[PDB]
């Protein structure tokens, strides 16, 4: 029953008078920390504060909430990232002076590793954020394509997808594949393959390797 | 703080509000609230709190104080449900259950009553659109009530003794993110070129069927 | 012809690149189709035009008797200059993001604004309405090829103008850019300018009313 489009509206409905790039900068850099604090805390509801705000979040990380019923319009830690991702997008779709401001401060660590940068477009860059799948239309299919590569280059579980495979797109179309022309999904794929990702590296050891 | 809206808008605040209370809302809480509002306004005027919480037929709301004389001019957050918004929000929720599938119209008919609409003898016969539009804050969603909230506050300023002061609020308002709202579209859209219904609906407020006794008129 | 459009550009950057700024790129992209008269009227094979400081020497084929002239390669026509400047701008905002917003204000494209593009829809699209942008589809993600294909589809044009566009080599192997992958980002670049409506701009909303949009 959960409507991923309505939740964001409901999200901006509450906090989206306090949101600025500064709090978006702290959240993404400390999400995993929040995932861990939520993993060890034992309150099904937990108030988290990222740079002033302020959020009340459902704890599904505590080993005994991993499979709870999650109320639709209840902002989880993943859902929040999606909404913080979809929000930045909007401020970059609209006044370009904001995007160049967004570039300076915010850092998507899941994009930095893998080697993305803002240099390749915010749809791709902000697309590495978990939860951006809830908005495949806003992010040009980059979440569906980003996790596909990880399945290929890396070998992430085909199962950990299936969650996105279901997202949906636009109105009538149940996303799937041909439903919405694969060409626009194919392009995004070809786009990410251009960046590759690899650690390193720069010097060769004559001692061995 | 000063002009004008900043943010805004109310569609988002509404769909967030149904997030908070939508689970346990019934035509029964509306029946109580829409009646109790008058008195609720008074208690908020009496109590010294900046933002209280009241229960009406069960729920359960944390509301913002806007009638207490010290807090009238103060700023209000967006998610902060002001009773006048609460009146505008709920009024939409009934309008959207009605305009969904009929059945559910029937329950709002037997239960919910609009006291500001019944002092003009309205009833559901006049199409839920018109009746519900009488509710305070109904101007926040002009389309969800077919321009009626704009007309009524444009009707009792003329056919009654009100000021154009209570029209600055009514305007500044969007008709689905609309440039040129004033009156101003093509075909004199709805405004007056569709209603003539607050005109056809009489002064009424008679109070009792004849009644024809020793009294002038009527 | 003899010239690879990449060689002419890098040569063009050597002469004027040292002085090229968004400000000087504005003046050309306003005096674009109105410089066609200056060259047509003056009977000189090469005129030293001025676009806010610089300072380029445009080679003339706008003259009706200079159609018989074959253009050299290190030479620069108005079509070439436009295209080159169109690349430099995109080129310069490919690096940094912080330098992209600079373009948003200081520059404006006459061709893209009419058909209803705007910067919002991407600088690759927008700058890709410029004449000579086809010379660099690899940089404009096939947008110059697409627009040309659109203004001949819904609208109507001669498919003979399309001839000059279908010659540029995306890079090698080669002139196409005809299939590869797949076939060539096209379609994506095609129906994306499909998503932005033809809705001719201008006006100020607006009712009408008596007749027309």
Image (cartoon, coloured by chain):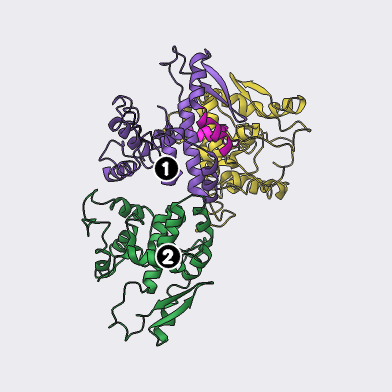
Chain colours: A purple, B yellow, C green
Residue C205, position as x, y percentages in the image: 52, 60
Residue C26, position as x, y percentages in the image: 50, 66
Residue in the picture at 71% in, 33% down: B66
Magenta stretch? Answer: A8-30
Image quarter hosting the C terminus of chain A: top left
* In magenta stretch: residue B28: no
Q: Is residue B93 visible?
A: no
Of the pair A21 and B125, the residue shown nearer to us: A21
- Discs 2, 1 touching: Cβ within 8 Å: no
Image quarter hosting the N terminus of chain A: top left
Same subunit under labels 2 and 1?
no
From the viewer's perspective, tell me whether residue B132 is left or right of residue A129: right
Q: Is residue A23 visible?
A: yes
Residue B188, position as x, y percentages in the image: 53, 57
Where does label 1 land, which residue? A123
Residue A101, position as x, y percentages in the image: 55, 45
Residue C131 location, quadrant:
bottom left
Where does label 2 land, which residue? C13
Q: Is residue B149 above or below residue A45?
A: below
In which chain is the residue bearing label 2?
C
Q: Secondary structure at mark 2?
A: helix
């Amino acid at each position: 029953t959960f409507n991923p489009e309505v939740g964001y509206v409901a999200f901006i409905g509450k906090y989206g008078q306090q949101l600025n790039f500064g709090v978006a900068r702290v959240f993404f850099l400390n999400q995993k920390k929040a995932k861990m604090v939520l993993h060890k805390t034992a309150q099904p509801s937990v108030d988290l504060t990222f740079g002033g705000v302020k959020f009340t979040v459902v704890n599904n990380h505590f080993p005994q909430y991993v499979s709870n019923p999650v109320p639709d319009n209840a902002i989880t830690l993943h859902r929040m990232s999606g909404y913080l991702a979809r929000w930045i997008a909007d401020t970059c779709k609209a006044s370009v002076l904001k995007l160049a401001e967004a570039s300076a401060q915010i850092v998507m660590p899941l994009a930095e590793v893998k080697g993305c940068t803002w240099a390749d477009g915010y749809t791709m860059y902000l697309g590495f954020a978990p939860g951006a799948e809830m908005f495949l239309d806003a992010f040009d299919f980059y979440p569906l394509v980003i996790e596909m590569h990880r399945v290929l280059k890396d070998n992430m579980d085909v199962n950990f997808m299936k969650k996105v495979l279901r997202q949906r797109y636009g109105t009538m179309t149940a996303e799937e594949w041909m439903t919405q022309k694969i060409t626009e999904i194919k392009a995004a794929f070809n786009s990410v393959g251009q960046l590759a990702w690899a650690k390193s590296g720069f010097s060769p050891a004559a001692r061995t390797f």
